[PDB]
Image: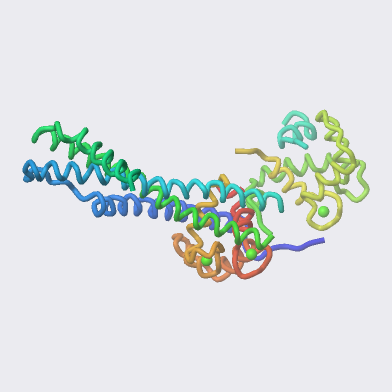
Length: 118
Length: 69
Length: 158
Ligand SMILES: [Ca+2]
Ligand SMILES: [Ca+2]
Ligand SMILES: [Ca+2]
């Protein structure tokens, strides 16, 4: 045997339907906020290149500088990628442990059955 | 040691082999290219850097959930 | 607690509530107390090609039984039809919104965060609104809505 509730159940839905509407929306903002942190952060590491003024020994030594960096960075990127990978495992691993701890009827078919032709 | 000379030399070689024949105008062309790829990478890193962060968080809420059940 | 169906029930037209009455007043013929016990749900299932065991049946009922009667009354039957109404958030998605609530990244949505979030919406959040949601959410009552509760809590929410 059990009892009744405090506020209109239809309302509770509308808030729930709204807490999400916002969060979903507040996510889009955290997202548009990232795309912006990407540009500004790339403008710091990946400074813009102004060749217009460089000479030959200037242009070459830089081409050498760059060629040299490409490898250093592709490695940094591997290490993180490395870890983000270990995590997919990790996350999918714990996701498993939790998982381990944790007929058919339509409405109209029934109504059809009870009332007849309605 | 000797094995270490090779890495140093063959490293320099790679630089020579790609840039040395390039001309004033072809370098600008190369520097652009090279920079462009350096950037592309630094960006691939970012999204990952971000990925890794949300991951720190995804996991944590997992350890939370677990201890609780 | 609460539900996406309960609201659906309050949502049925006065014309709707009626046909279910009929459907219900028939579904009960030959029933002593005037409620749907297995013997009755059995009768109809059988018209639908099914023939569940008492157990499979009693279980079909407990999912709707709210007064431990062990049988389905109109209101309950009322809910039962809403449930069986029709089918139309993914875990992955909610996992992301829950994150948007948890502002202190402790992996738990607490009163403060709930309220903060609760205020984000245009609607005039009353003192009752708050106490109630936090009430359906915290099915364990530990002060904070945990990921799993946040799941069952937002369950079905369009
Ligand atoms: Ca009952
Ligand atoms: Ca929190
Ligand atoms: Ca809780």
